[PDB]
Amino acid sequence: IGFGAANFKEINASKSDLPLDIQNEICLYPDYLKMAEDAAGNSMFFFARKEQVYVRHIWTRGGSEKEAPTTDFYLKNNKGDATLKIPSVHFGSPSGSLVSTDNQIFNRPYWLFRAQGMNNGIAWNNLLFLTVGDNTRGTNLTISVASDG
Amino acid sequence: PTPVSKVLCSETYVQRKSIFYHAETERLLTIGHPYYPVSIGAKTVPKVSANQYRVFKIQLPDPNQFALPDRTVHNPSKERLVWAVIGVQVSRGQPLGGTVTGHPTFNALLDAENVNRKVTTQTTDDRKQTGLDAKQQQILLLGCTPAEGEYWTTARPCVTDRLENGACPPLELKNKHIEDGDMMEIGFGAANFKEINASKSDLPLDIQNEICLYPDYLKMAEDAAGNSMFFFARKEQVYVRHIWTRGGSEKEAPTTDFYLKNNKGDATLKIPSVHFGSPSGSLVSTDNQIFNRPYWLFRAQGMNNGIAWNNLLFLTVGDNTRGTNLTISVASDGTPLTEYDSSKFNVYHRHMEEYKLAFILELCSVEITAQTVSHLQGLMPSVLENWEIGVQPPTSSILEDTYRYIESPATKCASNVIPAKEDPYAGFKFWNIDLKEKLSLDLDQFPLGRRFLAQQGAGCSTVRKRRIS
Amino acid sequence: EQVYVRHIWTRGGSEKEAPTTDFYLKNNKGDATLKIPSVHFGSPSGSLVSTDNQIFNRPYWLFRAQGMNNGIAWNNLLFLTVGDNTRGTNLTISVASDGTPLTEYDSSKFNVYHRHMEEYKLAFILELCSVEITAQTVSHLQGLMPSV
Amino acid sequence: VSIGAKTVPKVSANQYRVFKIQLPDPNQFALPDRTVHNPSKERLVWAVIGVQVSRGQPLGGTVTGHPTFNALLDAENVNRKVTTQTTDDRKQTGLDAKQ
Amino acid sequence: GVQVSRGQPLGGTVTGHPTFNALLDAENVNRKVTTQTTDDRKQTGLDAKQ
Amino acid sequence: DLKEKLSLDLDQFPLGRRFLAQQGAGCSTVRKRRIS
Amino acid sequence: LENWEIGVQPPTSSILEDTYRYIESPATKCASNVIPAKEDPYAGFKFWNI
């Protein structure tokens, strides 16, 4: 979701840098490069991906700075301060594109005719791995119970 | 015999053997501050941005110095072997997202708003913290010689003197090649801003003080060789997102024939009237990005259909699509903060880009007939040297004088120092990717091989996962 | 060409013609006739431009014109009318009002300049073509054109 | 614009560049043969087959504005009530081109 | 065959009204709804439905 | 003015190859097919 | 042997060079740079030009 992938646990010591759901948890990503290299190809028979995003707002962190832009970039002003103090990190908020009835990749039978590896779909070890993720379908559900019954 | 005066398309004197190779580079990573080089202690931190043309020099293994198990391989003096690219597949490994850039104190007085209060005379400062989304684009181009870019600079003014101190500089176009750490075009005209922004408030902090290049497609399409680019692709969308106004004093306002004065108003207009927009990239997709898509080159756009002259390749690949910055927050004491302070957490800023390169080169023997040999003189001075066809006079037939213990004082001083010879592209610098060993002959083995044979018809793996819906 | 409204504004001129009482219903303590002008013009909006939408650098092979003249350079002359606001973006500049880099940041020291620059190229694939000069055809041109 | 006694052409992004491509007369040229059209039978001309206008510059959007535009109010529902027009109501206005 | 030709510069159509009837909108940080005054009309812009 | 910057060798220029390409008389066919 | 195009590194036409309009404008660079284009040899001396 919008930010680089990392076990944020060691990157956010502030607790204010992530959306509460994602925080303290590890953000993975598909290392397509690795998958395309394995001789076996066991990693993936085939695969599909559709993802759109774009900036929607632009914000600024609020941490003290250990490295400001040198005087060769920042020109001081009257009654101003020698060095810049307010942090200059500009991360944008990730935006999800409008979703359609046609864009979602599902309910669509995938006929596998030739895999991308030397393994055209052989269930070695009588086992299969299905990695399916999409934030398209999901919408949260609210509720409201009386505090007395 | 030296008759020819016009160029001949490279296919005519180039024989194509039917051999193929697969050159796969191991994944490349680089990380660092998005904006400007940082300096902690006595070491540095390369300013690695998402808006810089990564320019690879893929240096090849000289073909003409290989192994020939047979007599069929070209005769030692009739012909020479080289490389010819057929396929290229630049792979970009990172999570998709949009690129943002800003600046601590930008120069924007006011915007396109109708209910905003009236413009206060400019105060000593009007700068503010500014967000500014990148103007999304993607550029890929393969060739023999480095790609050329264009930009605007200030041309020396004439002796004629009607000059003043604030007088505007004359402008002029200039060419240059594209190196490894150059700037992508983000919304503003291309120029070594260094002489255009004397205010330091006119650019996004990352781009400032650096030169913005651009692809001079016009120039590339004119070179006879075509060495400039074998092929190339570009996709870029942008549009205005806000409209702002500079904050500088004006040396030229609209004459009274345009501006109608008002009661108690002022004779001449004083607040500057420059309206530059801020460009925001269109939403990026999983289909728009031009990568991981093997490019089969069947005919180049020049007389050179992919001949690695000088056993060298130039890959100029730039896109701000993949890039997204990475924030961090370390406690200023080393111990998790018990309470929330504005001083305790130090915000760090690291961003990271990753590539991969894959080529399907083929072997190709150029004949060496008096005529064709000659011909290359005008096509290129340098590749002849690799051939070794040119003569070097037998002057080792001059007896120079060696000495023993050239150190002894009575003996000659031997003060003079030999100077090492320069390389063709040593003044300029760029990422250097060596492929001399990471090259092979088994197409089936690699990713881009099957991808190749598949299209060929000789496939153990055909690229089809037909989906009906 | 694409466009669409992006804001909606109102002129500020006195009105010589307001909507009659059959359209405007008066209110308490209000005024008999409407005085504030009611002109609503929208601001033109240019939508996002692409690498594919722009019509250029794309050789146009002319195979049949739309007139009785399939590309004959009568009078050995051609007219190329080409206009597009797609490429263009303005260029700002800032020179110190004294010639020396500013040590402090003033609103008066840097003079904002304006420079914008446009570049073209033209390429044609003309072919040779001989018109016969028979009494009949010769004549014919009298009414087609006086000058050629 | 006008600095000193010289000018500066107002070069905008919204002006029809109209080229007059003047050609080399095809009728007065060197005929090294006889099959070349007879001197009084016919005349040669030019015929365009291909045209390729190349535009070299970085892509982007065009903006234009004005120091004091005439706009009293807009299509907003929570904006305060319209004050009688003052002596002036003009403001600095941004206005993106209609591509 | 029929070919209706429209000769004019392209653009969007706008329409408004001196005093429209709109009390409030879909905004979350807007102050609380004041009881309707004698009048709540305002000058209204309204782009055509192309 | 184009009175002198006019030639007869189609192969030489950018728009020439671009032309011959379509024609079938090609030293450079306009194809850089991309599959994805 | 030169103009004739018999022996040369590149076609004169193939090379792309700048050219401005209104080169007298102070926005633009001065006319002296005009000398870069190949220069007539007898330019030092002068005579009636027909």
Image (cartoon, coloured by chain):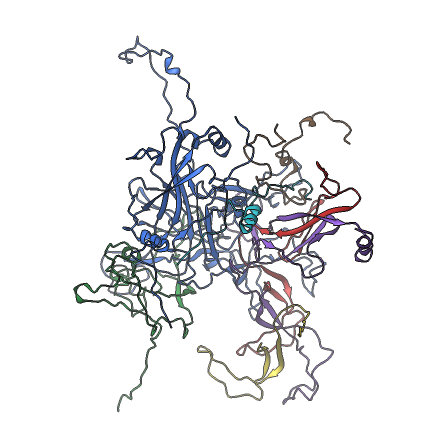
Chain colours: A green, B blue, C purple, D red, E yellow, F cyan, G brown
Q: Nearer the viewer, residue B139 or C41?
A: B139
Among all residues in the image, which is located at the extreme front? D35
Quadrant into which the C terminus of chain D falls: bottom right
Q: Nearer the viewer, residue B299 or A87?
A: B299
Classify residue F2 as left or right of residue B276: right
Q: Is residue C104 above or below residue G48?
A: below
Q: Position of residue E43 (x, y in %)?
A: 60, 79
Among all residues in the image, which is located at the extreme top? B410
Q: Nearer the viewer, residue B450 or B129?
A: B450
Residue at figure coordinates x 61%, y 39% from the top left:
B157
Q: Is residue A98 above or below residue E21?
A: above
Residue A14: quarter of image: bottom left
Residue B431: quarter of image: top left
Q: Position of residue F16 (x, y in %)?
A: 57, 46
Residue C28: quarter of image: bottom right
Q: Position of residue B67 (x, y in %)?
A: 29, 35
Q: Is residue A13 above or below residue B78?
A: below
Numbered label tally? 0
Q: Position of residue D49 (x, y in %)?
A: 63, 52
Residue B119 in view: yes
Residue B351 in view: no
Classify residue A47 as left or right of residue B317: left
Classify residue B30 as left or right of residue B218: left
Q: Is residue F30 above or below residue A135?
A: above
Q: Nearer the viewer, residue E30 or A139?
A: A139
Among all residues in the image, which is located at the extreme bottom? A149
